[PDB]
Amino acid sequence: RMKQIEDKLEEILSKLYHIENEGARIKKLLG
Amino acid sequence: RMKQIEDKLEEILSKLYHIENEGARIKKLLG
Amino acid sequence: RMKQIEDKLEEILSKLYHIENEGARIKKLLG
Amino acid sequence: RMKQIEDKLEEILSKLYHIENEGARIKKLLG
C-alpha cells in the first residue's frame, strides 16, 4: 500500500511544479 | 493509519486542482 | 511515527487554504 | 517507507512556502 501513496505524492509534486510555474507566468506578466 | 494518509493526500490533491483553476482565471482576467 | 506525518498533513492543508485564499483575493482584486 | 513519506511531505511543504511567497509578490505587484 506504500506504492499507492507514492503515486499520489508524486502526482502532488507534479501539481505543485505546475502551480509554481503558473505563478511565475503571472508574475512575469504583471512585471 | 496508512488509509487515513491516502485520504489526506486525496484531499490535498483536490485543493491543488482548485488552486490550479484559480490560477487559470487569474491568467485570463489578467492577460 | 504516524502522528508525526499527521502534523505535516494538517500543516500542508492549512497552507493550502491560505494559498487558496490568497488566490481569491488576487482574483477579486483584478475583477 | 514511512520516512520516505515524511521526506516527501517536507518537500511538499517547501514548495507550498514558495507558492505562498509567489502570491505575496503577485499581491504587491498588483495592489
Image (tube, coloured by chain):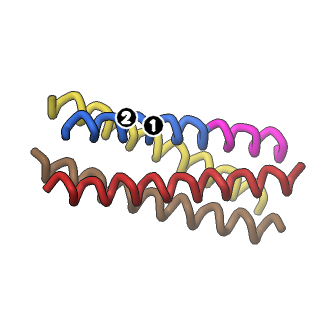
Chain colours: A red, B brown, C yellow, D blue
User: Disc 1 on helix, strand or loop?
Assistant: helix
Q: Is residue B31 left or right of residue C15?
A: right
> Which residue is situated farthest in the bottom direction here?
B28
Of residues C11 and A17, the one drawn nearer to the viewer in this rendering? A17
User: Measuring 21% from the left and 56% from the top, which residue is drawn there?
Assistant: A3
User: Disc 2 on helix, strand or loop?
Assistant: helix
- Total residue callouts: 2
Whether residue B19 is situated above or below residue C25 in the rendered picture? below
> Which residue is situated farthest in the left direction here?
B1
Q: Is residue C20 left or right of residue B1?
A: right
Q: Which residue is mark 2?
A: C11
From the top left corner, tell me how far across and down residue C26 is, in percent.
Answer: 70, 52
Q: Label 2 marks which chain's residue?
A: C
User: Measuring 41% from the left and 55% from the top, which residue is drawn there?
Assistant: A12
From the top left corner, tell me how far across and down residue D21 is, in percent.
Answer: 65, 36
Q: Which residue is mark 1?
A: D13
Do marks 1 and 2 share a subunit?
A: no
Of tags 1 and 2, the one toward the viewer is: 1
Give residue D17's quadrant in the image: top right
Of residues A10 and A19, the one drawn nearer to the viewer in this rendering? A10
Task: Count neighbours of disc 2 (C-alpha within 10 A) and say few if under 14, some if 14 to 19, many if 20 or more.
Answer: few
Q: Is residue B16 left or right of residue B27?
A: left
Dots 1 and 2: beta carbons under 8 Å?
yes
From the top left corner, tell me how far across and down residue A28 is, in percent.
Answer: 83, 52
The question of residue D30 being in magenta is answered with yes
Give residue B30's quadrant in the image: bottom right
Instruction: Name the amino acid, label 1.
Output: Leu
Q: Which residues are magenta?
A: D21-31
Q: Label 1 marks which chain's residue?
A: D
Q: Quadrant of the image for the C terminus of chain D?
A: top right
Task: Count neighbours of disc 1 (C-alpha within 10 A) and say few if under 14, some if 14 to 19, many if 20 or more.
Answer: many
